[PDB]
Amino acid sequence: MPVGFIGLGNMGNPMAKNLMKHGYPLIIYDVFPDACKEFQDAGEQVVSSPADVAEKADRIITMLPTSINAIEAYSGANGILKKVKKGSLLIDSSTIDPAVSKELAKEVEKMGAVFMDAPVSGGVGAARSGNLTFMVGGVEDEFAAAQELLGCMGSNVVYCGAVGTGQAAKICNNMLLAISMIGTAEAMNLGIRLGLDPKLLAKILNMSSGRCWSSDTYNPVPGVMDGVPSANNYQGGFGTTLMAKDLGLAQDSATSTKSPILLGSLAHQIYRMMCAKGYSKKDFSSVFQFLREEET
Amino acid sequence: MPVGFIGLGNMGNPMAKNLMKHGYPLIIYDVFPDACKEFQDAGEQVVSSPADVAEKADRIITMLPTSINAIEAYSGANGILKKVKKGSLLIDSSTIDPAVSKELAKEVEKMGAVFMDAPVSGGVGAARSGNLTFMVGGVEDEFAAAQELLGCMGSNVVYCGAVGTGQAAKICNNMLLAISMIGTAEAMNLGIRLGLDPKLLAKILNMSSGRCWSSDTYNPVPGVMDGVPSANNYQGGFGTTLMAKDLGLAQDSATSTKSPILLGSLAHQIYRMMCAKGYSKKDFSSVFQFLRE
Amino acid sequence: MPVGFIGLGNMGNPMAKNLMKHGYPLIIYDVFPDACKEFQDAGEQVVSSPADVAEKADRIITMLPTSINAIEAYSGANGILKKVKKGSLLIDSSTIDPAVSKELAKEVEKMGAVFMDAPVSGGVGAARSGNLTFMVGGVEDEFAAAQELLGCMGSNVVYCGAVGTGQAAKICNNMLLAISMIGTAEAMNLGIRLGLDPKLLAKILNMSSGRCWSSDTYNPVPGVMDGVPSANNYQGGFGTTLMAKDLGLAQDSATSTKSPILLGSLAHQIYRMMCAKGYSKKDFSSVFQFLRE
Amino acid sequence: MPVGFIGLGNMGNPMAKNLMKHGYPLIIYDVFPDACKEFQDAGEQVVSSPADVAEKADRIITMLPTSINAIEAYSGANGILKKVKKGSLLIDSSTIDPAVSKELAKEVEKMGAVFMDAPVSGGVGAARSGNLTFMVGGVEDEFAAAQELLGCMGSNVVYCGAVGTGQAAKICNNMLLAISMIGTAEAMNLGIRLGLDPKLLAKILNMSSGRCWSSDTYNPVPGVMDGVPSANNYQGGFGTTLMAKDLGLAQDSATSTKSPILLGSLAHQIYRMMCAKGYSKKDFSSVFQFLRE
Ligand SMILES: NC(=O)c1ccc[n+]([C@@H]2O[C@H](COP(=O)([O-])OP(=O)(O)OC[C@H]3O[C@@H](n4cnc5c(N)ncnc54)[C@H](O)[C@@H]3O)[C@@H](O)[C@H]2O)c1
Ligand SMILES: NC(=O)c1ccc[n+]([C@@H]2O[C@H](COP(=O)([O-])OP(=O)(O)OC[C@H]3O[C@@H](n4cnc5c(N)ncnc54)[C@H](O)[C@@H]3O)[C@@H](O)[C@H]2O)c1
Ligand SMILES: NC(=O)c1ccc[n+]([C@@H]2O[C@H](COP(=O)([O-])OP(=O)(O)OC[C@H]3O[C@@H](n4cnc5c(N)ncnc54)[C@H](O)[C@@H]3O)[C@@H](O)[C@H]2O)c1
Ligand SMILES: NC(=O)c1ccc[n+]([C@@H]2O[C@H](COP(=O)([O-])OP(=O)(O)OC[C@H]3O[C@@H](n4cnc5c(N)ncnc54)[C@H](O)[C@@H]3O)[C@@H](O)[C@H]2O)c1
């Protein structure tokens, strides 16, 4: 019973592969055609557009970079909504503006289908293993159905409320993360410059009120925690570019809902600075490197 | 074998009581005399100055508000250093500027005594139960001795390095808390205004990369968590005034060490505002009230 | 030769009046109908919708609050673009998102008309006297035509580039204004609290590298300058609500163009908080009153 | 009638030269001895310490980098106060912590001399020409005397109040400058990236509510204005190191007076970072370079 997948990059590729592990035939499409080559070999069908995915697939998933990509993929001249069938389940696991999710939801429900935002927590690793967290928004009746499908790609699938709530939950956590990580980087930098041994300061933080996931699970000072991007030149990880994108969404939503985010705004600008300054492909925890003094 | 205690407020009072529970005679002093009244009843000796505590006590503890108070309590005209005895152990568990800790350390070591900064993590509750964390700085040989004494008032006593490193650790930790608490607050306020139930957003933060002490142990959003100040109009707890003082210490250390603290600076200024806008006596998680429309 | 005017609030009312002073018949429309009553008395024609202004007016001006208002006024079910005539000149002097200006520009050009964003500098006063500055974007050949019309309402009309550049010019200015006003407020408060007389600190600021329009022309500290809003409890002036709206524009355009605006972002949030804390109707210079204890 | 001058760097050298232009014999000292070599050739006396300046000079001026330097130059083992004479006039035109100015003032007054803080506005250019602004604090009777002397080096000499008020004034002006300059840079960077022509955007800023000294006299965008550091790769001018120093003085005063400074703090932190990143030897207007992609 076929499943449609549109967009097969860093999260999409392994996500799409796990659906094949659980035994689903896929109808693939991607605007970068090289990205599909691997799937045509696996036995799966590659098509020429989103509309052509919809014409053959009763329920579809979309893992695209940002809002304009989803607007295009769905509403475009050769988009999904041009040939989506009655009662179809469309799931967008991209991270995009919630307002845009609702807009798409209105246009899908106009077509007699169901739409659900389902952005993801966890990176390329969790994507492969299948331990991603899905934050799901939409008509609650349909959540049962979506859980069946999303559970193949992920270990946690949480209902967040109406369409848009999934994006809002993703965006809020990333903002807190962004803030806490820059904070850890600063507390750590100040302490080291005050004479403390990083390993000990990190200990003190991690047993006190300062403790957070940044300090205890993703520590940005090299030589403190093994297994994290700081141990490995901040390679791979979750990309500064993406942190900045997600922060940018938080800024858009903060402004529109007239929500003051003092620390969040600055987190956004710091990451935006980092991207213009050669950190864009480095892990977001490399904010510590950015704070840390250069020699003369 | 007598122990000297100078400064008996919110942390000092219960700390001093726990030393009595483990069976130490106390030589009490406080510039606010009413604060002593309770101890003169318990059988303890109240004196007229710090110098007079030092004249009678071989090892002393000081729990004072900030730097100027410690500078006065020690170096003052009738301060400790006027009558401290050879080989005495002086411990300052105030949260003050590290630089000032070193300056006192130099003046104590001049007098042939030992000084150690030992600021505390945990609030009034931990103080009473005796589960405070002490972050201790000073000459490492002396740490053994200090652990013996501090362990009566606290459950964790950690060596941080040379004199000043304890204040360094307390100050830094409080900055991360402030940044994170305001962070959690901004995040929850955002999500609520985007139409999320707070109990569900907290769940998500807490099973995710956002998780931190502020969000999973001290949530600032009324009705999310039992047994926290947001459950009770932000009474008690750790006060905005004190938070703001501590972040001031961070700001000044950051300046002195030339360390960029962008968020830390905002955190400082936000709590300074709250002190001016009637939050001074509320718990610092009340920053969420301050952002909430 | 008729001129269409949509939206007659604080800037719109006096702008519309100055076009009557130079001798133009007006075709008025406003979603708040009481706002029109004054013009039906002057002899001018009030209509039921923007579309109905278009049906009667060869060149139209729109002075609306923000983006969605322009999007609706033009593209709406009974909007301008429903009945606009070949070769018409449409001028939007609202302050809105540049991106939205371009979008309307494409939609107007599709209908064989000309569109031009022409936001304004100067307040209600400049509006009345006719000394507003217009920042104008659009196809440069059409600038001559627009200057003829806008010059009735304003004393300076400057070409900024393609459609969107006017909004981008207004938005960047109001961002620098906001940053500098909060700066002046902060600097003055710091000096006052450091024991300076405010009038002296202003003298110094205004003869030195700190001088800016905020300090030498619109000074936020009551009693430093006569005739500025701070001399009359921040009544009238340029509204805190609108400044936040404009800073929201800067913010969202900074995001879209990936432009780091650190102080700018803070300015936005500070003004955001003021709206929620009882400054929304007060002049934007009231940030001083908001900082002061 | 001899004048003592201690510290002959970027401001000191030309200041000291203007005193020679008005015809004063100078008794020079500087911890960097090469800095003196030029004055030994002019006929002036170089000495081996501040104390040795005081032994020969009835009224002295000190143009040093920061607080510790003044503390040392005055109170040091071979400092001024070791051999200052009755009724002498000591003037410190360094930019330092006001609290430290008062401390010195008390120590000078104890020795029967007068002390006056007199920090300066205007850079290396105004220094040479003699158009610097002096902001003067101290006992008001003595202001007459100091004006006679300072007027040789500067065109404006303003009384600010008691000792420390000069520093107070310098420090709040510079904080406002930092905020506006970063503001301008942010404003200009955002306009450019929204596609404006810079020369135009500056024109608009400079005829609108955004206008300020930063944008109309010292515009950081290369090629908008002639004559400013941004025309010459940000060489010379007013160094990022010193701006960061002055904003550290604002910050520490801001904390000490419990004054909220959200933007001044950010300003401080930005300039801090720029010093960490090889902007230190560059004029402070180089903040535009730093934000720009
Ligand atoms: N990478 C991570 O560690 C991580 C973690 C959590 C969440 N996310 C979120 O997941 C989303 C995508 O992650 P990713 O790293 O796989 O992105 P990606 O860019 O690597 O993959 C997206 C793919 O979509 C394709 N695409 C773009 N527009 C399209 C269109 N109109 N039609 C068809 N295909 C199109 C691109 O060719 C690309 O291969 C983002 O929104 C991101 O915020 C990423
Ligand atoms: N309150 C908390 O939850 C908490 C937690 C950890 C650390 N701290 C830190 O511990 C320190 C004290 O906290 P607190 O709430 O007990 O303060 P407090 O005001 O409640 O207690 C201070 C006491 O010291 C006295 N005092 C002031 N100057 C004195 C002097 N010169 N000589 C003798 N006594 C003097 C005061 O009269 C008062 O009784 C602070 O530095 C604070 O930041 C507090
Ligand atoms: N007020 C000032 O001092 C000042 C100064 C310079 C620039 N501005 C800018 O001018 C713009 C508008 O200023 P204002 O004070 O006139 O705003 P305003 O709110 O006072 O007036 C706008 C009017 O438009 C009407 N309106 C709203 N939606 C409409 C619609 N869809 N169709 C037709 N009419 C509609 C409203 O009823 C209202 O009366 C803002 O973007 C602001 O930034 C204001
Ligand atoms: N540079 C400017 O455009 C400008 C403008 C206004 C105000 N200021 C203020 O002026 C002050 C100094 O300005 P500058 O640019 O000449 O600095 P500078 O570094 O060029 O000059 C300082 C001089 O004093 C000497 N010195 C340092 N410590 C000494 C000591 N203990 N005893 C004797 N000499 C000592 C140094 O060797 C140096 O020659 C600063 O405090 C700054 O904020 C500078």
Image (cartoon, coloured by chain):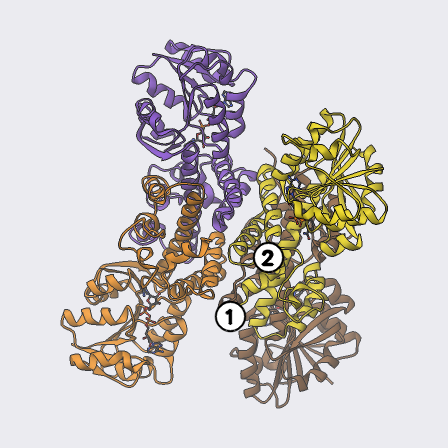
Chain colours: A brown, B yellow, C orange, D purple
Which of labels 1 and 2 is toward the front?
A: 2
Q: Position of residue D35 (x, y in %)?
A: 46, 18
Q: Position of residue C136 (x, y in %)?
A: 29, 62
From this view, report whether residue B164 is shown above or below residue C107. above
Residue nearest the viewer, comparing D170 with A213: D170
Whether disc 1's CB lies below 8 Å from ligand 3 is answered no
Report the side of D288 relative to A60 (left or right): left
Residue nearest the viewer, comparing D36 with B131: B131
Numbered label attached to residue B281: 2
For the residue marked with disc 1, what is the amino acid?
Answer: Thr
Report if residue A205 is visible in the image. yes
Q: Residue at x 70, y 32 (%)?
A: B51
At mark 1, the secondary structure is loop
Provide the residue designation for mark 1: A257
Q: Position of residue A74 (x, y in %)?
A: 56, 78
Specify the subunit that label 2 lies on: B
Category of crowding for the residue at label 1, using alpha-carbon neighbours closer than 10 angstroms: few (below 14), some (14–19), many (at least 20): some
Report if residue A203 is visible in the image. no
